[PDB]
Image (cartoon, grey):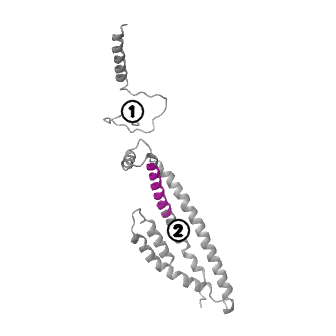
Amino acid sequence: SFIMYAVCFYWRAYTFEPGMDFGASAWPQFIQGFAVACFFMPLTTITLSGLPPERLAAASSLSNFTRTLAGSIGTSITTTMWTNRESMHHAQLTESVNPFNPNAQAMYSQLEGLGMTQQQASGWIAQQITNQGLIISANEIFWMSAGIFLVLLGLVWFAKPPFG
Amino acid sequence: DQPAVQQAATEVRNAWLALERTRIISPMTGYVSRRAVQPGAQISPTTPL
């Protein structure tokens, strides 16, 4: 399951594009189906292995508490990383948009062809840069997640086999 | 010093300044950063160089 989760995230990393159809973000989840399927049942069977029937409640409570904490932490980290890396990419992109550059005055000419003002055209270019940065930053997070998965692989082997 | 002759002298001066300005001079000591001018380009007084 860990290997399958790394595969899915690397799949998303090298295939996201501005003009991607609905199918480009539907195959990776079809693959992630396997990874999710074989992660909850086995790991939960290991988690509650060998404990007496009476204590199953407390163990379940502890497991759920830890899992919810992990979910909240993950959301908190990921959102901030997404926005901050978007800002960094925005900074690195807006540099190219200056005078002294063909295929930069041409864009302004085509924009003014449609009747937009100069300020409106500038805003439109800024919005496009923002969108590209979000896609790049979003794909940088997926790559990091898959890499992190590759290391978490081997920890599951430290558990003894008393399963039952 | 006659009025008629001086009128034409003014036009001569304007034309001469026009010709002397075909050479573009640097107004400040410094270093060149961007260069968007190539031989054969068509230049107006609104095109950065």
Q: Mainly helix, strand or loop, the magenta region?
A: helix
Q: Name the kind of residue labelled 1 in the image.
A: Pro
Looking at the image, is A49 positioned above or below residue A77?
Answer: below
Q: Which residue is mark 2?
A: A145
Q: Nearer the viewer, residue A23 or A62?
A: A23
Is A50 positioned to the left or the right of A146 in the image? right
Instruction: Name the spot of residue A48 as percent of width and height, x first.
Output: 62, 86
Q: Secondary structure at mark 1?
A: loop
Q: Nearer the viewer, mark 2 or mark 1?
A: 1
Looking at the image, is A150 positioned above or below residue B30?
Answer: below
Q: Which mark is residue B45?
A: 1
Which part of the image, by quadrant, shows the C terminus of chain A? bottom right
Residue A52 counted in the magenta span: no
Instruction: Name the spot of residue A73 as percent of width and height, x first.
Output: 62, 69
- The magenta segment is A120-138
Instruction: Name the spot of residue A115 as percent of width and height, x first.
Output: 39, 49
